[PDB]
Image (cartoon, rainbow, N blue to C red):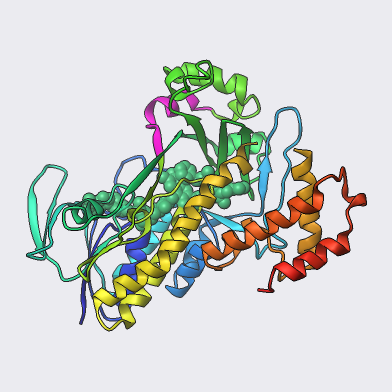
Amino acid sequence: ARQVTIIGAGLAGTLVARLLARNGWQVNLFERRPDPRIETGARGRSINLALAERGAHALRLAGLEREVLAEAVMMRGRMVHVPGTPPNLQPYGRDDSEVIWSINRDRLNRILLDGAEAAGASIHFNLGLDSVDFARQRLTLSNVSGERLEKRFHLLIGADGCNSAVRQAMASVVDLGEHLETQPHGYKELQITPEASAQFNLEPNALHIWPHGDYMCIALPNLDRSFTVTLFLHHQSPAAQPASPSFAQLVDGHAARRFFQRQFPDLSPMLDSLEQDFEHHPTGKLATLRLTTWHVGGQAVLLGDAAHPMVPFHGQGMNCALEDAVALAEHLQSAADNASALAAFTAQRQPDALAIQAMALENYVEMSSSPTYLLERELGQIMAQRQPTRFIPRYSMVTFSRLPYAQAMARGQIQEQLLKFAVANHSDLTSINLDAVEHEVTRCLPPL
Ligand SMILES: Cc1cc2nc3c(=O)[nH]c(=O)nc-3n(C[C@H](O)[C@H](O)[C@H](O)COP(=O)(O)OP(=O)(O)OC[C@H]3O[C@@H](n4cnc5c(N)ncnc54)[C@H](O)[C@@H]3O)c2cc1C
Ligand SMILES: C[C@@H](Oc1cc2oc(=O)n(CCC(=O)O)c2cc1Cl)c1ccccn1
């Protein structure tokens, strides 16, 4: 049997461990954290993720989709909150087949861990990768207390997240051609209790947004009607706008409360533990990291966040990481040798990872914000109705289909260009020749 060592029992690592182990590979998975399945008296994390078609299909191939979805809340659309007006729902898709699912990260990880072990993978927790000796095919791991342990490896998979130790180790043997692009927004997680969400009639079957231009809040529901709120706000106020809100101005929980009372007045009464959450939850960082190289011969490869950290605004980090795990397991299973599998995997996935990194950055303006846009959107809706296999809004191609990300971006561009020229110099729909716009759709967009 072929052997593989995987670093990181996260989302991509555990899925790839299950896929390889059920195909007879000898799989050893190393994880820095403790096993979340061992019940402790600790107060566990309430992180929510939006699972879409790419991630759902990956779980489906692994036989874990039904179990994951039993524990997922349907989000039918985007509920936009602007003070004084009732929330505007905005369906994501055409029917209940075109939805996103809100899943608790810890519930998903336990399912994936059980799945990897059921398939035959051995999982070793409380062991963090420190360094790799590529020449001797040996790695060094340690616990939190610093006690070191060495292990031999044949194939190394770096599924160890955005601050990947495998990626850092690879940089000593190859030029990764690494380009880090920082993002000015930090993030803070806040809670809405089931009692508060019910009292304020917050819809459980939707993704909620409180747009505020340069900053915003989002909320994802849980099975028990609680919601995890995420505030996106600049770490620092720019030089040009020193008065503009930022985390640097929010000195403590009380300042955060004052800020929410002023800027998010319909949201502040639902956040009962705002002051404590603000002070005890750390401010997260966001970034895009692009690498020219994802592998070292046939010895090691990166996937998921280890390969392509992206900004969170499209909810595609996990979906892309799960899609990578399927592609990696497929390439490894059927290749002539590991070196061929890793080069083929990298060549296939890199253009698509670059496309989703770009689309995730573009989605911030779509969430946090024009009559021209409204007319384009209305025309876009008519074209999707008239031509459903040709005109598919970019959000739907990314979220509800498995079309390669680079193709969704290219088609999305043809559509934006088509709508722009069609609405130009028209105040409303009545002056636009709809049949001529439809002819342009049939001429420029091949059916999918
Ligand atoms: C709060 C939050 C919400 C998110 N919401 C969404 C969402 O709505 N939709 C979406 O698609 N994506 C979302 N994402 C992004 C998504 O979580 C990631 O893109 C995804 O988890 C990447 O999967 P991964 O397996 O590559 O990495 P991870 O899931 O981060 O797993 C990496 C694993 O490696 C372990 N590890 C790290 N360093 C070492 C080491 N040196 N040695 C050993 N083990 C190590 C970590 O402990 C972890 O278990 C969210 C991210 C955050 C932070
Ligand atoms: C929860 C996640 O934030 C998102 C998840 C998301 O899922 C999605 O479908 N979208 C787009 C929704 C839309 O355009 O209507 C989306 C956006 C964000 Cl910021 C997050 C929290 C904190 C750190 C990193 N990630």
Residue 390 position, x and y percent, is: 71, 69
Residue 254 position, x and y percent, is: 48, 16
Give the quarter of the image for residue 220: top right
Residue 3 visible, this orientation: yes
23 relative to 259, above or below? below
Number of marks drawn: 0
Q: Magenta segment range?
A: 272-285
Q: Quadrant of the N terminus?
A: bottom left
119 relative to 262, above or below? below
Q: Nearer the viewer, residue 266 or 303?
A: 303
Q: Quadrant of the C terminus?
A: bottom right
Residue 40 position, x and y percent, is: 29, 46
Specify whether residue 309 is painted magenta: no
* Residue ID at (66%, 47%): 78
103 relative to 189, above or below? below
Give the quarter of the image for residue 286: top left
